[PDB]
Amino acid sequence: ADDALVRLARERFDLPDQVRRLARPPVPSLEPPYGLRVAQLTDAEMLAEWMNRPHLAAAWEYDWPASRWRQHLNAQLEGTYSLPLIGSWHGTDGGYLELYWAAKDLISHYYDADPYDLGLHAAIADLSKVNRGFGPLLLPRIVASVFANEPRCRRIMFDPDHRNTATRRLCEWAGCKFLGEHDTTNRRMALYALEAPT
């Protein structure tokens, strides 16, 4: 039972040749004092702790034991679908993200996805900096980086819980195109698309 390979619930396998052929999503970059790096299986303990916190346990529902987060991380790292990232500033890790190919994800069943569509999940470990509007500040840079790395990507997908008004409003103020509420495997979400700059 030495950490067997688990199956990511949201991963789609009935992919077209163009999509299946896609390598793992590029690692975006943030200029100092901010940094982004690929997560490591050793980040499991830290992430499990982060995700078991009030604000994240309710929004991600991924409040599992280190062992499990280890499996989630490994499953992503071993494929070419989702890329887990750690965000830092001033030598400290304070954020977790997931940059994944939308065409290889569950959300591609609720809208016509372009082959290079990218999705982005993100969380701030500091319950504090959340109430500070830290995310709204960094997100724009991250998105720009993401778009920069993949000139082919026509949009970045956001899928907050339909009840997450705070996040939905952010999507709205940013100019995202609303793509409806959809009942999915385990929850009802509000799908938003941030079109790449023209």
Image (tube, rainbow, N blue to C red):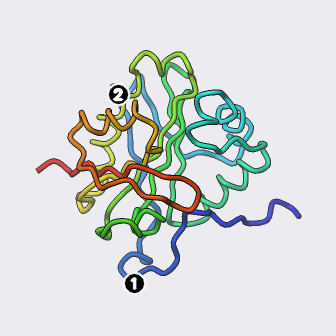
Front position in the image: 188 or 11 = 188
Q: Residue at x 49, y 81 (%)?
A: 14
Q: Is residue 133 toward the left or the right of residue 60 in the image?
A: left
Q: Is residue 151 toward the left or the right of residue 20 in the image?
A: left
Residue farthest right in this picture: 1
Q: Residue at x 46, y 17 (%)?
A: 131
Q: Residue at x 65, y 31 (%)?
A: 50
Relative to 41, residue 100 above or below: below
Front position in the image: 1 or 133 = 133
Whole-percent x, y for residue 72 in the image? 67, 54
Tell me if mark 1 has few (under 14), some (14-19) or many (20+) residues whose alpha carbon lies within 10 angstroms of its own: few
Relative to 174, residue 68 above or below: below
CB atoms of marks 2 and 1 within 8 Å: no
Residue at image mark 2? 136
Q: Residue at x 50, y 48 (%)?
A: 98
Q: Amino acid at mark 2?
A: Pro
Q: Quadrant of residue 44?
A: top right
Q: Quadrant of residue 77?
A: bottom right
Distance between mark 2 and mark 1 Cα atoms:
36 Å
**Sequence-earlier tag: 2 or 1:** 1
- Which disc number belongs to residue 17? 1
Dot 1: element: helix
Q: Amino acid at mark 1?
A: Asp
Tell me if mark 2 has few (under 14), some (14-19) or many (20+) residues whose alpha carbon lies within 10 angstroms of its own: few
Whole-percent x, y for residue 85 in the image? 52, 44
Relative to 69, residue 35 above or below: above
The mark closer to the camera, 2 or 1, is 2
